[PDB]
Image (spheres, coloured by chain):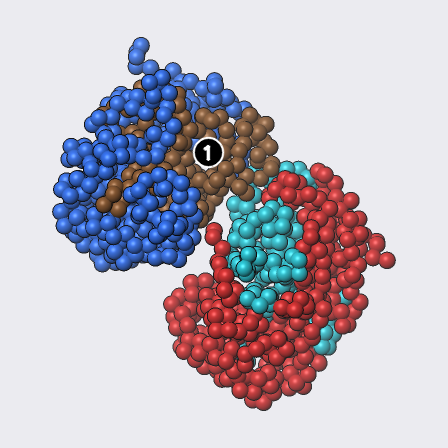
Chain colours: A red, B blue, C cyan, D brown
Amino acid sequence: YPPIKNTKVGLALSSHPLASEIGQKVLEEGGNAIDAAVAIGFALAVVHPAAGNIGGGGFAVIHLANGENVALDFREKAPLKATKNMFLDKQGNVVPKLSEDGYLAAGVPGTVAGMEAMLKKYGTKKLSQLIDPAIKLAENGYAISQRQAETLKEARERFLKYSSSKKYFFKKGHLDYQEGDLFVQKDLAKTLNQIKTLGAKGFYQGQVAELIEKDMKKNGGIITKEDLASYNVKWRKPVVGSYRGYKIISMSPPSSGGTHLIQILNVMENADLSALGYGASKNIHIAAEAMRQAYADRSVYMGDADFVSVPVDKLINKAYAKKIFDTIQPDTVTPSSQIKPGMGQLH
Amino acid sequence: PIKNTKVGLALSSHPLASEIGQKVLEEGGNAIDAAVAIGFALAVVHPAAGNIGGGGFAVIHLANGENVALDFREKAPLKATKNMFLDKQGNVVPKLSEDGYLAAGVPGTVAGMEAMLKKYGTKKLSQLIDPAIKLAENGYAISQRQAETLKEARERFLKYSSSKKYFFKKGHLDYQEGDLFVQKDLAKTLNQIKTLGAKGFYQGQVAELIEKDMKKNGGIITKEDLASYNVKWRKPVVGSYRGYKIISMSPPSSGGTHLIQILNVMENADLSALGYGASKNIHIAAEAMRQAYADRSVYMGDADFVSVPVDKLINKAYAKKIFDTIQPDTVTPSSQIKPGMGQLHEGSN
Amino acid sequence: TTHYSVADRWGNAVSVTYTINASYGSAASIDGAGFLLNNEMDDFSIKPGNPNLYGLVGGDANAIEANKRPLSSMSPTIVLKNNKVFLVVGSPGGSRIITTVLQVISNVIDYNMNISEAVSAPRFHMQWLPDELRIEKFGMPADVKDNLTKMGYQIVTKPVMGDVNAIQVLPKTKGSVFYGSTDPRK
Amino acid sequence: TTHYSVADRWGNAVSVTYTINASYGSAASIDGAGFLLNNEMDDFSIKPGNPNLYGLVGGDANAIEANKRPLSSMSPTIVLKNNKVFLVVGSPGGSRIITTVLQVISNVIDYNMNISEAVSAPRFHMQWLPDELRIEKFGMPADVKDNLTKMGYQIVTKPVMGDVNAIQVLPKTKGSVFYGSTDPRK
């Protein structure tokens, strides 16, 4: 139960021991939270391939020593050739797994751009140094954990469909990796070294960009050098809220999380949850009904704010939350079928 | 959960003690050898409970299928008397049975460790105790929790010169998390045991130190008490619960008896039906517990000195009767509970 | 998806959630580069009313367009108190991310749990569609489920939700103390 | 009090619970020997009806007598399933030892929890006198507490109970696997 503790350099926590240690060591060596975050970002792209990555994207919410709160959007972008019904057959019907497995299901990767973006703006150490640990792990390998042997096995069927993956995630003869096996990733190392040397350009340009485009074209994908060269992170303002005297700073669009998190919290704030304590059906009911309305709202008002109008300010307005709370009945629920996005309000 | 499929596991409340035990299993010792090394290790790294100055029980399952129990519980001193903790008016003398030298029973831990080792171990006490000696001599790091407990016991330690010297840094300062704690006198005592075995504690120099400090501070333990200390191999209490066999400690402990008793009552209900935490299941376990502790207050004691109806307390027939008294949706106030439920009456006794 | 939290001695705090969407993303790699490609496009509404990998639905707001970024549920968050770092939290889990993060925060602020307790605590989930109250094994006792079922909820026990890596910073007389917690779920 | 469990590859299992009674026992050490003396005499009934440190009471059976051993609640236990070690469990906690140990056993056998879950699960306690149902913080939700209270229980929240160090052995295709768990309460 006892939480991890530190009273000197702070904490750097991730879902993988090697990556967390790598980040912690950056803190011990003098780097700041950003330096450590960038170091962790690349480490996880090596030791936790199921999620950690350089081929995906994500978000970063940051509180700076000077009191400023910023959000970094390095989410993937639909390719330049992507279309509204690109995953439907010639009858408007969803083409099975076309948006789940394969090269066409991929958006332009932003992770690498994101790491360099936050480093250049708020970091203090050089990328070349913060990326060395991951490079070492990719070059010399690491032990396949118990959980990894599993997840890797549950994804075997998918890997098999693609030669590229068959070569990187299987031992000779396309055999699954077992717990304890030493997993080495030479090509990933090369790519990482490219970034270490040329920075983000080592990924979105040159050989790596070449490999991406040619392999994409060769496999029915649509990502091209044009896409990579045009990928751009976006520093956005975080969505902000308050909860019983605490300031909530979370991710704004293209993420819906921060908005609905603050929305639901706003509804719950109208009740004294502390009174009945954790796990009381009375408190769970209030939170669940708030969630119910928020997810309904999500299905209609949420999208990339750069392309559509998203009523963030309205959804996080406490008056709107108060209107939701007042509809919550003490011992009965509001069926989802009777829920109406926006409640009719939002105007 | 931690795991092992090679030599097994040795688990304790202190990582250094657990490692010492695990190391014994790795080096080829059996469960008893590892238990003995841990017993001495905890007496160094976990002074709040680990010890050589107290006592306890060991329940053992041997590879051949036999189940035995070792009683190394302290004994009231030879000069102990029924009202020794009461004043002339028959009222409890505050703290007399809790703080100080008169609150002590004759220690059995050391006799117990040696007893189980010589009967079921495979290694020499001399080697199994070295890790502990090393920790007492070289010292170990005070943990966060340990700093907390030492601090809370501060007022009690201050009452005695011996403890003020051993459990406080120079100047009566509380040990802090991270401080290296060295125990030279303890190492000296552990070395006597390493060289002479149990006799290194119950006799010779150590026995003298004990009797001397006792006389000086109002305690009644003497060299005779120590030389007379005896462990006892007893039959464990045995029971069953939904197919599984329950092996636990018999008197002088009431633990195994009431554990089997309470589980016997619970066995009459299908707890799986509602699952963990259901008030319906808690009610049955709680009312069973209520009757068990009521029974404890009257029928439990050292069976060598008093008649203890262990077999009747763990009989599923008695448990069924207790179960039947449990009323749905309502408790039986403790004021209304009758120890024994009229099932433990041996005539007019 | 995976999330990591970082906080230093200077007062900086970084909460990062990134992913390739599903486990191993699209399962397809870039030959010669050695990295897996994401299948983030599935976070787009590829057809009105069509539920994706997490049961989420959408209309026009989240339809596919060139260079548009697909809607996400990732909730990297930082909670402040007196403008100082108090909590750094986030988690993976598709649609359940929002509710998971929300519960950890509520656990600390509403029930005064330390970050370890807040993270370990059983979690529930409601996402409108499907109309069910998702819970975890051993997470809710009979008495609670009975009362919720009476209210109209359709309770379903499913795999544990999330993998929260959080940090709690508390002001010390001379400096600050950092408390962290990894999730016992994964 | 403290408990430790050991199980080896030959099939032996040793469950040991030992103590000097209270935290640091009598708080008095043997000068020149470096060890603390137990305050085990308090486990005796020093006066009919007088509650000891754990609220336990007694009469003749547990009265003081020279050379007699004071009654204990220590419950070092071993559970078998076919004369083969299944669980090695025990715990400190005075009067609460008995209930702590049986709940862990129950959690495994009745609710099929693995040893880690079994140990971590909240615990309750009833010892007849005082007439109260003792629970742990965050251990029992309002719904359950309300129903138990309506039954007649006087619920009280007190410090966490115990420090279980347990081992679970499960037969494997080729041999046995040993699962262990320390107590978070430790």
Q: Residue at x 39, y 73 (%)?
A: A182
What is the count of numbered marks? 1
Q: In this view, which residue lies farthest toward the right?
A: A347
Would residue A125 be seen by someone viewing this image from the given angle?
yes
Instruction: Using the image as rendered, state which of residue A143 and residue A233 is in the foreground.
Output: A233
Task: Name the spot of residue B207 as percent of width and height, x first.
Answer: 17, 40
Q: Chain of mark 1?
A: D
User: In the drawing, does residue C124 fall left or right of residue C64?
Assistant: left
Image location of residue A136, percent across then percent down: 44, 78
Residue A168 visible (yes or no): no
Residue nearer the viewer, D186 or A335: D186
| Rendering quarter of residue C77 | bottom right
In the image, is residue B35 above or below residue A251?
above
Q: Residue pushed farthest top?
A: B348
Circle 1: element type: loop
Quarter of the image where one finds residue B267: top left
Q: Residue at x 34, y 57 (%)?
A: B180
Q: Which residue type does callout 1 highlight? A: His
Question: Which one is nearer the viewer's eye here, D150 or C37?
Answer: D150
Q: Is residue C66 above or below residue B129?
A: below
**Is A283 or A236 nearer to us in this picture?**
A236
Mark 1 = which residue?
D125
Instruction: Judge left or right: residue D144 versus residue B124.
Output: right
Q: Residues within 10 Å of mark 1 (few under 14, many from 20)?
A: many
Kindly give the residue lying farthest to the front in the view shown: B171
Look at the picture and state if B66 lies above or below A31.
Answer: above
The residue under the point 38% across, 70% down is A181
* Residue C122 at x, y percent in the picture: 55, 49
Q: Position of residue D23 (x, y in %)?
A: 37, 40
**Residue beneath the point at 45% across and 22% down:** B324
Identity of the residue furthest to the bottom in this view:
A206
